[PDB]
Amino acid sequence: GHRTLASTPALWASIPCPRSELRLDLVLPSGQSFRWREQSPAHWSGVLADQVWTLTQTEEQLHCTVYRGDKSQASRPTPDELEAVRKYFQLDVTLAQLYHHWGSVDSHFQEVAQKFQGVRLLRQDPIECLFSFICSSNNNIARITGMVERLCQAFGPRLIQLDDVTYHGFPSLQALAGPEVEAHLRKLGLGYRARYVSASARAILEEQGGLAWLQQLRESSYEEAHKALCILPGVGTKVADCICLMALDKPQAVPVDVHMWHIAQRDYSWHPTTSQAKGPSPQTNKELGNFFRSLWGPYAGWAQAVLFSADL
Image 1 (cartoon, helix red, strand yellow):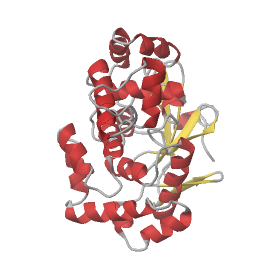
Image 2: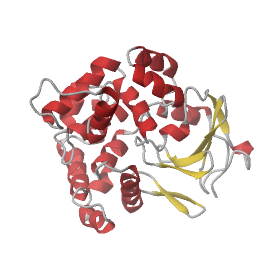
Image 3: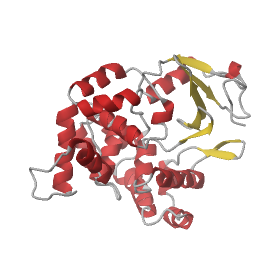
């Protein structure tokens, strides 16, 4: 079944990484990616780039193992595979300097940072991110996590089965654009958003050129990327911001919803000023987003991530 470092050490490869730079337990289930579960104490297993991985860490090292199936000899991750993991967690970025900066302009963040170290922003795949946040609202992590799993088990390739868990890759655009998708997804419990999955897949696979379109937004400006995504069915300002931040390399993006409003009110006593509205709205939400961006800087999105992990 699921591997453990202690049970099959010869099948694990390590990546130099202090616990001060990463805390799997605070990142994997914090609402960025919904593809990871701690199937075993301190061991997180999930799907990363069409491959099942299990990850665990020691004080100074992030241990990794990948499952290859019956077509290939079981062996430790190769240098390139490990590099894929490093990019996923964006380890090239020194968290220390970010935490230092955020704390220097925000006493509240400084106090929260003390108990919540190693919170970083994952670099997810565009398609996986886009459709995960479109298939369901995000009011509850447990909820969207179940919906994403149903989405993958319904149109995602079967990768492998460990113990009583069948892992599936993320559905391809062609699979989501296929007929009867909405109907089947609804039968699964998805809801009306099952329509956006199908519609968006078809909109991209066709009217947008296809996969290349998303990969392009990664290089486009945050302003272009966000505006481009909003044309897709089910993609609003908030969802577009998540994708920009989590998958299109736009760290300054700050997804604003009722959750962030609570944080702003509870921890910053923030109040709208540029808008007459006192509660959430297209105008006040943008002002709120700009408030944190101007406060925290170009990586405002990562700072938000730290507060979210702390609030779980």
